[PDB]
Image (cartoon, coloured by chain):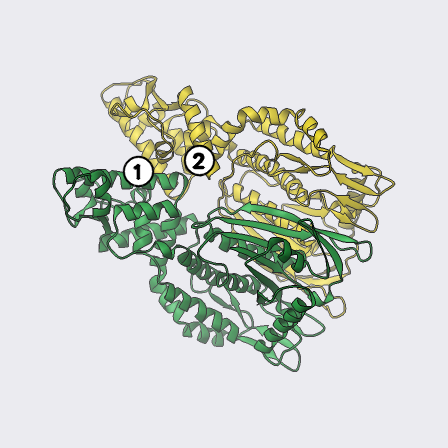
Chain colours: A green, B yellow
Amino acid sequence: MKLLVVSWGDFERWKETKYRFGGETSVGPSTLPILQKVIKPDWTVIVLSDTIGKDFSSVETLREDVRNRVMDFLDRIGAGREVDVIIAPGIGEFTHGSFRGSAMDAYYYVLHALSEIIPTKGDLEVHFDSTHGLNYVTLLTYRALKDLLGIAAVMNTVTFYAYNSDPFVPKITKELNINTIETTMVKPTPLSEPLPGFDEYLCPYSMERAEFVRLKGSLNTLKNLRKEKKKLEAWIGSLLFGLPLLFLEEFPDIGRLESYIEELAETWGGAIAVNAEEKAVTRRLAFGSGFGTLVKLLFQARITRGLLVEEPYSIEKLYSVSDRLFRGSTLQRVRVELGKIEDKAIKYARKGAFPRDIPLRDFLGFDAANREVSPRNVLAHAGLEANVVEVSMEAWEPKRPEEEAGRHTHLKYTPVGLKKVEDIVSRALKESH
Amino acid sequence: MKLLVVSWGDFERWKETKYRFGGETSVGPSTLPILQKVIKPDWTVIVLSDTIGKDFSSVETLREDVRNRVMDFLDRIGAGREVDVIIAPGIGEFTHGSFRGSAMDAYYYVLHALSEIIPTKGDLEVHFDSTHGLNYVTLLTYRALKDLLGIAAVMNTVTFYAYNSDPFVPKITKELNINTIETTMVKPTPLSEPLPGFDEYLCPYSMERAEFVRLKGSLNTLKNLRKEKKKLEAWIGSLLFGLPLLFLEEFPDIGRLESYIEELAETWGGAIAVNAEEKAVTRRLAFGSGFGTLVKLLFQARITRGLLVEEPYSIEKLYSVSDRLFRGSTLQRVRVELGKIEDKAIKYARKGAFPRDIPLRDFLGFDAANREVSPRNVLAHAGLEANVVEVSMEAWEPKRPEEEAGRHTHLKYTPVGLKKVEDIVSRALKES
């Protein structure tokens, strides 16, 4: 997959000029046609501001106005119609109208938009053109792209290239070169924010206190997220800290995440007041960090959903899951722990023994000291602490148990144990923020 | 400590307007006064393209010209004395001059500039304004800030704000609000990239390939990096993987890193050809990723120099170092491993036994047949692998061995062990 993303301003006010890029040459007002010719992307994404729109009879007429104007210009230049247009909420008082709201709305809207576009299977080569963009929309688009690509890198290889053209001088300019200003192999960065308190999903920009309290109090999301919060924070922690069994047992409900994001995103869109006479758009609700955390959580869930399997979890499965999610010293300590449990099963098997629903402590043969569940041991033993895990050996007739024991030995958290791990990991996630 | 960074283009062509910010109001051509009033910055930095320079006698007359007119403007709106100004290398054909070079030189030059300004001690509250910036110089400045603060976050609390104003639109604007476009607590991101091949410290932009090979061969930096490259990647690995004994033994020479950066910086500057008649600057050398990696490596070293304890390295010191340097599961893993060794030393101390210069495998009492040094065991056991570490206990008269053993028990890599570990960590960093 090759993805070209382009940050745009007022594309009608652009002058014709020449562009050099990849030994090719292009006469036109925009960088997009030569960028497509050289890079040959599988998909193009154009990111521009609401403040280009010249219609205030509706919020959906305002967008179709902008989308049409963009579709004309793509015919004007040689640009293909294979594109997505993210019409992001911009700010400021213009001659053709007025737009007010949180300036950070643009980030959260593009973040959510890009989460539904960037593929969640396969490698990503990403090209971002910033030549034509507004400073603040281009930073917030750059920030939103990077933050999602980082979650993508956990499971897949992600290369990111960024271009800007030579600055434009009215009639001195003969040919602007399109420079590469970044080429990066994107580091894997799993989500490491806890979900915030219920003040930080939607905030009131221009709305009477009681109306806001009614909208907030109407949201199913905030009600459910109260009871679910800890289990989701336990899942986030299982990627960050190297807990392969917690990852499987705590794997989120994608449908319920999809539900929360759509409810919050719909409430936002609905509270946009477009006053048609006086040419004015007020976004009376602002997005909060909690919306971005949900968008990112659902994107990390989609990226990793391919690893999930049914409820009997074998040491061999935990090995395979671990080799995708983890790297460096985290990957290696996980393998040593699975090693210790695996080697003990091989011993049990040579003796013709197959214990079932036995605590890991009894399975490894520990002393009667320390029945407490400390953060230390839960995090140091890749979440496979001896007082919280239950082991089951599915009976078989060994002949080479060294390669057979992994498929037949299953780990499970106890119902009591899982609650102790969720606290420790949830607290450890919040204490690292 | 509160810091204010701003991105500037041509600050003369800016009209008077009024700006609202944080229960305040101000009238001027720029946001800096009201930003400086509301935010009470302990220090301020301004990043401008050099492409606003007019007098092309040579390089020091451009930077001079640009610094003069800036220092005029900062008196016109009373921007105080607590200020640094970074004249970054821009490119393009302008009305009063032409500038040629890699577009990425402004990233590395500003990264270098910022690396000597940002405090490497105590917490940081960084405020960034992009209102008056060129797109690319503002994006590279933002990227350069984040890269360094991420390293500072290893050791200190770092909070970051970005601002941009409502657009100035000349023929309807009454007043412009200063919007906060970002509020973030900066995640600790240790340096996580190997040093590259000796092609990628300085690259020729417009130098004939025979002249480049000449000057690459005269740099004392690339010859001294030949030796150390592995020893430095080992150190980078020590933070990233949780190897606190390797962090101490491989702790780089800051004076020697300083001199490498300055030799690459002053070699780049000395390949800038200025033509007074053609009004044309040409940067014939471009900075490579490797220049960026050295600047970041020197920055991580200054940030953590405080953790380099005196010899010998005791289990108590390794605990102390570890507690500062590592978080989450990596910290808990390292603590359990030092605890294995400590608990052993306690048992020895109780029997009045004080083994001196004994391999860790004999101290822990291991089987034979396992003297191969694997990636797995070096990375999984916090670099304290039983075939590469030597233990000593300084004998004493114990009263509470559970408190004393920590202070009197010293670890170090064997000379053979350290070279194997360097190879394993260096390699693990390259596969990343």
Q: Residue at x 22, y 43 (%)?
A: A404
- Which residue is located at x 59 percent, y 29 percent? B257
State whether residue A109 is above or below residue B39: below
Q: Is residue B207 visible?
A: yes
Q: Residue furthest left?
A: A352
The image position of residue A91, as x and y in percent, is 63, 67
Q: What is the chain identity of the residue bearing mark 2? A: B
Q: Are marks 1 and 2 in contact (CB under 8 Å)?
A: no
Q: Where does the image place residue A142, in percent across and percent down from the top left?
A: 58, 55
Q: Which residue is mark 1?
A: A336
Label 1 CA crowd tier, 10 Å (few <14, some 14–19, many 20+): some
Left or right of B267, for residue A306: left
Query: SS for tag 1?
Result: helix
Answer above or below: position of B222 versus A3: above
Point out residue A212 in the picture as x, y percentages from the top left corner: 48, 73
* Front residue of this view, candidates B210 and A91: B210
Instruction: Examine the image and state in which quarter residue B197 appears.
Output: top right
Res. B77 in view:
no
**Tag 1 subunit:** A
- Mark linked to residue B428: 2
Q: Position of residue A330 (x, y in %)?
A: 38, 41
Q: Quadrant of residue B385?
A: top left
Which of A4/B129 is in front?
A4
Q: Amino acid at mark 1?
A: Val
In the displayed structure image, the side of residue A88 where residue A54 appears, left or right = right
- Mark 2 neighbour density, 10 Å: few (under 14) some (14–19) many (20 or more): many
Q: Which mark is residue B408?
A: none
Mark 1 vs mark 2, CA separation in Å:
17 Å
